[PDB]
Image (tube, coloured by chain):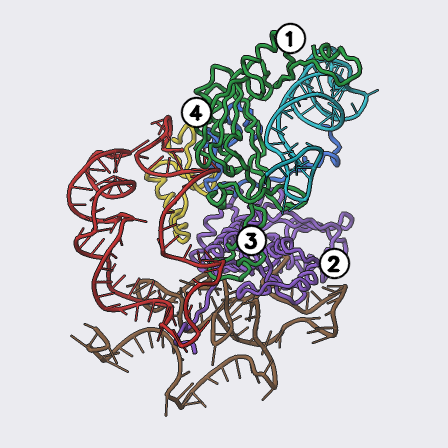
Chain colours: A yellow, B green, C purple, D blue, E red, F brown, G cyan
Amino acid sequence: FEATPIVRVAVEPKHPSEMPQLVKGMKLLNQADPCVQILIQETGEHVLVTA
Amino acid sequence: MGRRPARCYRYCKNKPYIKSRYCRGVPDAKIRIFDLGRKKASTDEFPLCVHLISLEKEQLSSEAIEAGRISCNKYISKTGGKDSFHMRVRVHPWHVLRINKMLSCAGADRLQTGMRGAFGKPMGTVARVNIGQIIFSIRTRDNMLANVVEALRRSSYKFPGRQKIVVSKKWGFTAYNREAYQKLKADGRLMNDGANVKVITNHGTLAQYAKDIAAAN
Amino acid sequence: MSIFTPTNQIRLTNVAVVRMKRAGKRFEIACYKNKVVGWRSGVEKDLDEVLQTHSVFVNVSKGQVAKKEDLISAFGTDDQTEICKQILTKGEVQVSDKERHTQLEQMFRDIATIVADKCVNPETKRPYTVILIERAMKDIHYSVKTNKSTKQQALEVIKQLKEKMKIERAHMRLRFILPVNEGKKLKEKLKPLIKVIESEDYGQQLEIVCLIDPGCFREIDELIKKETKGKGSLEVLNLKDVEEGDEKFE
Amino acid sequence: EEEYLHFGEKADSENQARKYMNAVRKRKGLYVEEKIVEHAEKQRTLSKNK
RNA sequence: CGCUCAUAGCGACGCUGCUUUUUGAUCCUUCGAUGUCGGCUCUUCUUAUCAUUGUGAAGCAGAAUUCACAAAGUGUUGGAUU
RNA sequence: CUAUGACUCUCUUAAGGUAGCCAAAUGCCUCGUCAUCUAAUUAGUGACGCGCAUGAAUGGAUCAAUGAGAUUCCCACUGUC
RNA sequence: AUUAGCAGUUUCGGGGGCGUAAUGCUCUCAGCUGAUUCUCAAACUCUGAA
């Protein structure tokens, strides 16, 4: 389940060296909390999405 | 001039300079506009005129004048509208102010800051007015008096010193009083001019005349 | 004697000094530090605002006012306002520290921006982000230089960033048309040395090649060609932001 | 701003509506802002009335 | 502007003052010689009051902040660098 | 576009700064930019260098020893607490 | 030096409404002309001061 308006947000690295960690983390989240655009993109490198 | 404080010039002194082939280096006047409201208004509809006068003899800065006009042009709208105010201001700024600059100095001096070659360069355009000389002037309908006096009042704050407000006894931008204005209509001597009245008068500048009554009529 | 009855003093300026050496003669002027920049940024605020004084000096630090002969000779005119204006436009300008910093800041942004134009492409909808690069630059530490151009600086510093590590930029297709005889020769040398794609040798229909560069390394790919065979039949140049047909490289 | 001075609301500008469309383009984005090339420019070389 | 709402708090263009703690302008005083800049020391005074005493406003609920009166009674620091 | 300028045009006067070196006892801006040293450094040192105005016996760069020379930090030092 | 509208023009300037569109009229706005209006111009002054 994604939202009907397709609500997006610009998730960014706080530190540049933490970028990889951030990337990893989204994937991890995906299993626990359902649905994020970490791969297969319509807008940007990665964006968090919800219902 | 907004650089200086205008204390510097609010006393009418020094014989008066001008723009010319002699004073070329002037800035441009602040007010280049003397047109507030409905200029295309007939003389036979706005029978009131109010005036604002400088109580004191003094200079009257261009900037100040400009400021004043938007106490009678914001306040044009909230009260009445464009169909009440007709303003020609009734003073301009021909006179100029010089500035012998010593701003150069902020730590030391070159000595040219001193009074050698003292004479200042043009900087600040300004008006000169006696006590009678009129400074604002709204020709208007006679259902608008307190809603135009308060424009004038507002303006007065933005002039140096003392400023008197008044209402005349005429149809405004005319010599002739309200008593002698009705004559014109009655005697068939009213001649319209979209703003002014020419007022038909018999005279002789010819050889044998009779068109001097039959011209404008 | 000095010690007894005033021991005397020296005095320092706090006004910008715009200087230009014309005909081996230094002319200078009296302006302020945070106006002289603003003039050149298209903030026309009266010339009389930017000038503290309208005169020209041989040295405005001490206060030696400049000479008519010197002026006319060096400018082709003795009128001073115009000369002052010219000086303001042309000559070196002293600035404050804050002002200086602003320029540096701007440069910093610029060098990130130039990197962002063409970035890493998994598809063609990923990074192209200025911010990350900037952050990286900040966190690696390198001297940002006003004498150095922005592009050059970027080129210099991307290498450094590479071994952080962080992969950056994407290549494009600068396309060519070689001759029949020399094209083959070129191919023989350019295949293992650099990346070459869409190669199709023919006897009648010439040879097409596509040398791989980002635009910022187009001297190295062409030099070899020049050495070997000279210029091609046609030489295609594309923009340094996108490759005309969407980037897919790196 | 001349147009605005005639006055019939403020639109096709910075607005209440542009709050929603201010900079939502960039969630990092496809590009820095917008990269596009065109060959519709130059009306004389194309020889068009369109 | 402060959602709204001119003056809670600010305040445009504009206008009037005070101050002598800035720097110029001036050259009256001194070139029969007022020892020039800072720091230490030490008192005194001014208030244009940062704190505290007492008061009143606030977009002052509490918290903290902001604004103002009386008031100069008591405080008003330790260091790097220069 | 290069950092820079080998280069090509051109002018001035014969040439137009090579090796090196550097905010130097030489950098106005200037408390330059970066790193370090310090809780904090207009100071110090090491980097950067279109250098207001470095540079080769007007000697350039290096440097052991030497120094009632000049500066920084640390340790012994605490009434120079 | 410089403010305002007015009128008379438009085979001369421009764009609209009126038969497609104009300068054919009528408009705001250019130019020119006529009568009126604002401030009069130390180096302007028909007049002219003790």
Q: Are marks 4 and 2 on the same chain?
A: no
In the rendered image, the vertical position of residue G40 relative to residue C65, given as above or below: above
Callout 2 amino acid = Gly
Please give the label number shown on residue B188. 1
Q: Nearer the viewer, mark 4 or mark 1?
A: 1
Callout 4 amino acid = Glu
Report which residue position mark 4 lands on. Answer: B150
- The one nearer the camera, B209 or C94, is B209
Q: Position of residue C148 (x, y in %)?
A: 56, 60
| Quadrant position of residue C24 | bottom right
Give how far apart the Cα atoms at labels 4 and 1 are. 37 Å
Mark 4 crowdedness (10 Å alpha carbons): few <14, some 14-19, many ≥20? some
Q: Does the image show residue B87?
A: yes
User: Which chain is home to disc 4?
Assistant: B
How many labels, in total? 4
Callout 1 amino acid = Gly
Q: Are marks 3 and 4 in contact (CB under 8 Å)?
A: no
Q: Is residue B96 left or right of residue B207?
A: left
| Quadrant position of residue B204 | top right
- The one nearer the camera, C94 or C224, is C94
Q: Are marks 4 and 1 in contact (CB under 8 Å)?
A: no
- The one nearer the camera, A40 or E5, is E5
Q: Are marks 2 and 3 in contact (CB under 8 Å)?
A: no
Give how far apart the Cα atoms at labels 3 and 4 are. 42 Å
